[PDB]
Length: 211
Length: 195
Length: 210
Ligand SMILES: *[C@@H]1O[C@H](CO)[C@@H](O)[C@H](O)[C@H]1NC(C)=O
Ligand code: PRO
Image: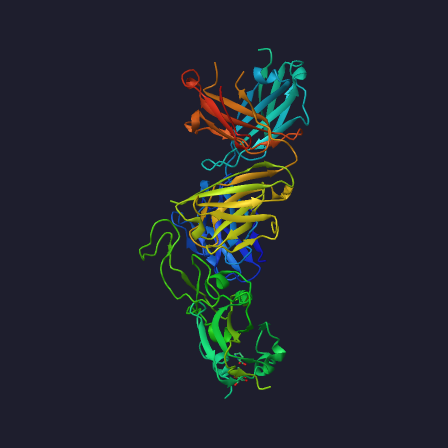
């Protein structure tokens, strides 16, 4: 087999920066190397074929070079829509093999989330479970503390978070947190609060169950 | 009359694999020892015969098929193999009787800056029959739309160049191949070993 | 011009069999080098199999003796027959023209190898308790298996401001995700909003007004 070693595993860069990814083949593959861009939940798109050739329709900020074992892929000036995972592929030898990928992340200025809180639906309560959802909308950086408070009591290990892929226009993230309770517990308490900490500022959205 | 293996193995120039060369060997004494005893050959594989016993045997005719492929393809020149070379360029039968002989020709067939003169067939609708040759250059139709002889989308020139540069990895280096096939028809045996 | 559309994905028991389909338009399957490539969740790309125009077939060592690649000329379709399936075979499976010819990939189909049963989703409104000038509405997609689900709004006519979240594996073994949309508060009484939820592994579509 021919192994494809890709570097780096992940990089973080600003809009406008020159970005360089390397691929190294474990033996000669001539110029038979392809570069792909994969945006989450989509198929890989070919950017560069045969080490240096731009696929038709691909912006000219993308380039590649190399022949033999050592290959480079370059974005001359990073754009927001360039958030993706990038793969090298050697295709002229079976088995066909890919690099491990380079996850490309964008650095930008700090952005405060718009915070929303949602009570359980009547429909769901009938099932005997309560899901309380807190939404953090269009923020940066990735890292934020989300804490659940139920009558000012700090919950632990009964919520789950998921973060969206970094936005391809404005480079922000979004987070949804779901607090999960039995129906009996949801009717035991009044005040439901989601606390968002970024830096030394905390923002709390809440609702009163009665009202 | 000694069999002209010199002209086969020591030729200045070799054929591309798609246009593989055949030379008939007839009416001569064939000394196979000059071959099997040689350090010159990195592949020497015999089928339906024992190489050590070659100098003892007589055949109706011998055919010497010769061509260039890249190092990592030499394995395809064997009965029962598949791949771009076996399927679309040069095919041995399952019941092959003969020998496959190969050696590295980097020093003769590579050039600084690359030698692009050796070609192979990349696109073909079906597999070659054993010992079939296809030297056609029709634009290959990869879609439903006819190509009408015009190279473009889904319309591929069927042949590709190897790119032999001396500093290539050995898998990408040129190898000269000679296939000797032995036929024993109901006819006079014109090619005999000295012993 | 070239379209590759995979199908056949879903939940299958360990040791079970599944056949994937790739319907092509704008190329002839039987005239081309055609491959399957797979991607395990959150992992890299792994080439699975190739078929040549002349019919030669090759396989990655990991699927040797278990998978068979094939085609139907009259349907212009590539197939992958997967037998003796293991948990490690859980992946999105892509068909592609590979390794030679124009570079084309399908959108992919997710295969889940698990001992569990297939479960369709429960869709619940996510709605706020005068509002602020920007209001949020959503849909909670609870207790489904396997992945994946897709969410649109007003049959895909509303895309601006939508955030459909990745799913989390709950401790019960079932998935849950949210899909939210931020809208101008002035439209909350004039326009109408519906989340269109598709769980193809259970053959269920849910449309829920909010
Ligand atoms: C080719 O030439 C060399 C050197 O003259 C000689 O040793 C060799 O045996 C020749 N090969 C054949 C097959 O006659
Ligand atoms: O016949 C021989 O001995 C030489 C060795 C390489 C080329 N042919």
